[PDB]
Image (cartoon, coloured by chain):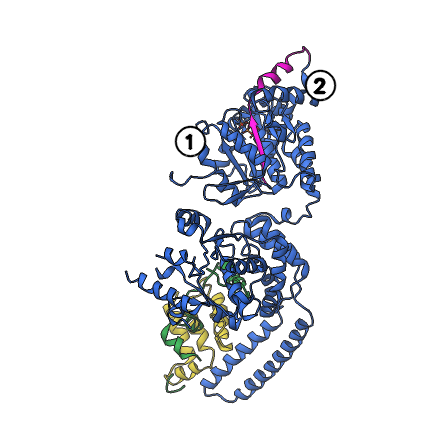
Amino acid sequence: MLFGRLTERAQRVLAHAQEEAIRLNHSNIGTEHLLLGLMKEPEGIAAKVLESFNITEDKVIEEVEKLIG
Amino acid sequence: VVKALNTPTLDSLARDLTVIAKDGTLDPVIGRDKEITRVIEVLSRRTKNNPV
Amino acid sequence: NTPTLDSLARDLTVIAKDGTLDPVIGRDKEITRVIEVLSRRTKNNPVLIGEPGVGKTAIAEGLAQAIVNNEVPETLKDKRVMSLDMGTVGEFEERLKKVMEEIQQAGNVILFIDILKPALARGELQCIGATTLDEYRKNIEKDAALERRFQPVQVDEPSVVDTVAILKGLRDRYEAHHRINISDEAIEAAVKLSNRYVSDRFLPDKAIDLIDEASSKVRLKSHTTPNNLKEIEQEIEKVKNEKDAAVHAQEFENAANLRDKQTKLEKQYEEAKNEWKNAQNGMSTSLSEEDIAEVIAGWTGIPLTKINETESEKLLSLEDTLHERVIGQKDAVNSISKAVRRARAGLKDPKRPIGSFIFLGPTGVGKTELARALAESMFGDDDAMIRVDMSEFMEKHAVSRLVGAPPGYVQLTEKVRRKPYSVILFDEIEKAHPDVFNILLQVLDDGHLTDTKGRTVDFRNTIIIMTSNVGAQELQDQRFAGFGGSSDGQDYETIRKTMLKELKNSFRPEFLNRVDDIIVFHKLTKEELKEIVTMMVNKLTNRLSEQNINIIVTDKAKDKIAEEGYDPEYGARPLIRAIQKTIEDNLSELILDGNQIEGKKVTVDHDGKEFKYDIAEQ
Ligand SMILES: Nc1ncnc2c1ncn2[C@@H]1O[C@H](COP(=O)(O)OP(=O)(O)OP(=O)(O)O)[C@@H](O)[C@H]1O
């Protein structure tokens, strides 16, 4: 039941993570890419969770870029 | 996220397998397709339809 | 109403009154025999003598059912049948007295069994036995009181036509369950194939056991989705999941669109299902004869290419198969080919064995190879051969081994019972106990035997071949009798007559009268071994098909290796040793050297001193 329950936005998050992995010259799809893929989907329920917690798009990108190499 | 969001006799006297398998918790049975097909072919018959 | 008898045993007339089970078919003679014996003044206790599994319970079921159908005569009219199982066996003796008293008082209760001697002496109980012959001759015959009170009745498996009638009688009971249209031609093919191979549990369970997968295969193949409904069902499921997620997301703007899409997909799925089921119902589930053959191919392991035959080209291809597997000496092949077809057609007596050939000649010529080739070309199974060595059958106590252990002490009959269609081969028949010769003569004449337990084995479909080493000294003298030649130029009939004349001196004159044809093997020459080497090379290449390696051996190497172990007495035994120690020793090292010759071509050539190996592309 891996792909039998994912919604349309769930696959969009995975596609965003996959396309961000190529640009960052990373051969491994780590957990740091799924976070970026989720942040670029302001339509899901999780979008309201981060919006209400003063979590924007530009801050998380630089915060995760600093941690990773 | 929370705030922003039938034959009952046999059910209690035994355990139901397809209910748990529906939730997607059991390990996927891989490589037993031949046995599954043999069992379903044997089971679908008027006589001698109880595979062992 | 005999309440005690109705509670301590199971009543059959109540079950037969409703008729929920299939009626007893093919037992129209056993019922009449039972009702005739029960009407006799003396020996009114019939016994169902027979091996378990032949349908002894069906006889009692039919006897009980005949009461409901009003087919029993006035002697057995409106009389219930009660069966007492062996699982209810002091306090035990206190119930049977009341049961027999109730039976005597009522007068319409018929006892059935699988202390009581005074009861049977006066004939107050019309019990019907169902024990096997071995127990009947061990516990009943030893008592004189029950000897004149029980009438033995022979109950065994019916005929093939009776089995066909039984299968056709219950056709509806199988066709109405899974809605399968069983063709008439499939019944006869199924009953033929079931008796051809499955002959262990007797009738009727060895013939009705084929209809469990043959029809189910086509039923399941025609019941699947041809990539039409599965995609629509997946789309419906994903739309339903998306709609549920939207409902739980408090976003009803897309809820209407999702509901409309789900309704449209449901309508499309209903239309597709209707149009598919109309097409499916437009045709019937007819059955072919190939399904039964496929099922029996997996039941016994026999390849489908052998089972799918009309039993007409097998005789023609027997000679070709024997010539291919056995190199040279076609006289024996032609002599045995003519005799087997006469018996197969029906010219020979059906009770007598099909083949009664005798193998004669020097050792190492390949008699076992010819026997295996014949068994494969006639029955299709290489391992369906039973070999009994007469070296151990030299004393008088050895005669009680192949026929079975007599009661009081604790082979061939037991093994041949499970495989009636098997080739039987014997060795050192010239040195055996005299009683074994009498047993073999009885097999060749009568066509069947009987063990100490009373069970009758079958030898009508068995081929008996006896290998004798006597007379080998005469053949070798003829080869060297004349300089520049041998006896190969002589006619085969003259040598056969001389060997037959020399054979009857040591054996019994009447023992050789049943032999269809005397088989005499020739000698191995230089040219014969060249093709044997080629056959060995071909077999080795065939055994290396998994590694995909092509091996070719030049005729020079074959000639060089043929003379390494040339000996008429040994035969072909040194050839295998020479082949294994020359080419295979180097082949194994090349295989183990990191797949050096994997997927390549290996050439064996003899330059005069050694065997140079060439490795190139394949
Ligand atoms: N023409 C032939 N082509 C190939 N192989 C042959 C040929 N003739 C004989 N052989 C081989 O000879 C071998 C001799 O072994 P086999 O056991 O058959 O001998 P036999 O002569 O029947 O004697 P025995 O009864 O003592 O075993 C056989 O295994 C067979 O492979």
| Mark 1 in CB contact with mark 2 (< 8 angstroms) | no
Q: Residue at x 32, y 61 (%)?
A: C93
Per the rendering, the colour in which chain B appears is green
* Residue that extends furthest to the left in the rendered view of this protein: C90
Q: Nearer the viewer, mark 1 or mark 2?
A: 1
C471 lies above or below C24? above
> Residue C367, relative to residue C28: is it above or below?
above
- As for residue C473 lying within the magenta part, the answer is yes
Give the residue at mark 1: C397
Amino acid residing under circle 2: Gly
Q: Is residue C549 visible?
A: no
Q: Nearer the viewer, residue C114 or C551?
A: C114
Q: Which residue is mark 2?
A: C489
Q: Which residues are magenta?
A: C461-484
The chain coloured blue is C
C301 within the magenta span: no
Q: Amino acid at mark 1?
A: His
Judge whether C37 appears above or below B9 on screen.
above
Q: Where's ligand 1: which quadrant?
A: top right
* Chain coloured yellow: A
